[PDB]
Length: 456
Ligand SMILES: CC(C)c1c(-c2cnn(CCNC(=O)CCl)c2)[nH]c2c(C#N)cnn2c1=O
Ligand SMILES: [Mn+2]
Ligand SMILES: [Mn+2]
Ligand SMILES: [Zn+2]
Image (cartoon, protein in one colour):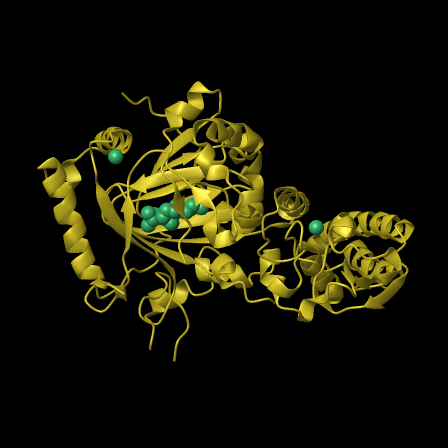
């Protein structure tokens, strides 16, 4: 038996409220960050086109077994068209229930999902699509291409809710990152079938995410507020300890399906929703979420980072260091990139970046004093941003270095961050070298330029 979590908040903004997505998200944040996820129904005449030929859209399916607490990975031959995938998917669901696909109630599919995942006798496997846009299978929103668009497609080209606009919109600081981090910054396309499932996870760097269901049967979500993130992790550590073995790569972290009733039993707040076609789901920083598809559908989702998020992004990279997990990008490098563009930044952005930069500079001053007292005397400026990420990771904690690192002539090519000076080599301290991107004297005017831009 299954007891459905309480429903998450649903917002129905008017057009005035809906027009600017970042202003609207900021307004709902007090309510929505208490539930981790929320649903947004756009005003009734915001309806972007869905004009695809299912016979020309191709993608490589992925296979999924459905066993509660079984380890699965994040995704990185075979081929379906959207038509043949849809036909396989609909026949699977109608054969599974011996009913037409739409008369299966969502409550029932939900019940049956949690039954089949917990029964070891059942060996159900399903297939799904998950990838970024490609020439073989593009975004569900209109994009610019030199094909003629209808005036209705043109209406939605520059919408803030056209998710293709997210990796380039001013108020997502992720847009400032020059590094090509395609897996994180670009929209993902999700082609679902009944019971295809996304395991419990938070987004990289604790970013927000936003998900739009273009068409098809609904997507069922479970969400946990960011404040209960460690509570949830402790519950999963106890019940599925195999998922917490230290992982060699970011593409090797383990995730799993877990009944939300199990989390509720252990006092973790969980909320649910059925996302229907034309609706958005927003996940907030560090809000765990999982779910499954009710049947054949097509969704598009993207990460983003508001100024709200900057302190949490710093807190996240700290937490990655404690865990020895790889970063997707350097947070400090992104801060300094924005500082170098201060004259062009939005004034509220400049004020918030400035506050994060002050913490960064004080933390960095203290760390350099600590390593100097360990006998590291030699030093040389180094343009960390020119190194491929895997050439500038701390040997100990895997963090991506940018502000500074320690090298040692006895272990050429290796780096540690300033927390792990004692982990690099066994040579005497005068053979170590501090490699730094900026002097403290470079840094204070960078921050000052942000204060000027903000105070205007
Ligand atoms: C079932 C698919 C189409 C799907 C996925 C998804 C990605 N990867 N896998 C395989 C299992 N691994 C993990 O879930 C890694 Cl954490 C599923 N993610 C998501 C999200 C999210 N956020 C929302 N809708 N949505 C989907 O409908
Ligand atoms: Mn099973
Ligand atoms: Mn997600
Ligand atoms: Zn380190």
